[PDB]
Image (cartoon, rainbow over all chains, first blue to last red; front, side, top):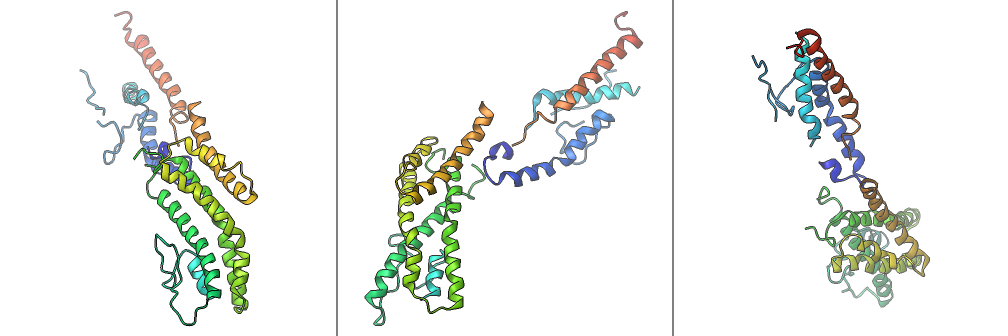
Length: 81
Length: 185
Length: 35
């Protein structure tokens, strides 16, 4: 929210670099459960946490795709069988 | 008396020039070795340093005190910070002139203060003109895009240094609105 | 500024393919349409 909060100033590049490096692990976390079906979590900084067979859980970002990742990871867990 | 005027005028005033917020800078003025001749030149020179301190104080006061966030446009807003941003870049040649004087004083310090007033005479006109432009914005608590008009009527000017100085700052204030326009449109 | 329209755009195109493979995998193997 600090990014949309100020962009028209000269402090925009420094904050842009800081957000660019602060989103580096989370994108890999997202990159895991889709492309390997490996739900990875370290300290609970990932937004969505963990017969009927699944006991995975759920909960700024687009909420249109936030539920979509929760269903996209479990689909990979189905194809492994 | 040569170096000390630079130390006062730079915005880091000494104890010879006791800064008040109701008189600005004032020399100590209680000597049997101070003459009326120095007095008038000093009093002319005092205005410029008082203006510079008020300018830098304004810029510091409204830039670097919040991230970007009262909702009142006279105290807060992106247009005002863009104004401060233009003002410091306008303030740059004053600093250049002060350093320029300093080098020649290190070469030979026996140069007169009249030459300093003679050099600094061009900013002596420019500073009071822009002073009222910032003072109106602070006084009337002007919100948003109306701030753009307030400089604008004063940037159709009839003196080249004043008009050219305000015009660039108005370009900065244009740019921030353009950036928001690049989203909403 | 940063938006999610340059990151989520190469992702949903893969999410759709994954879901299409799953709905295909249902019918061709467990024959739910037949069920």
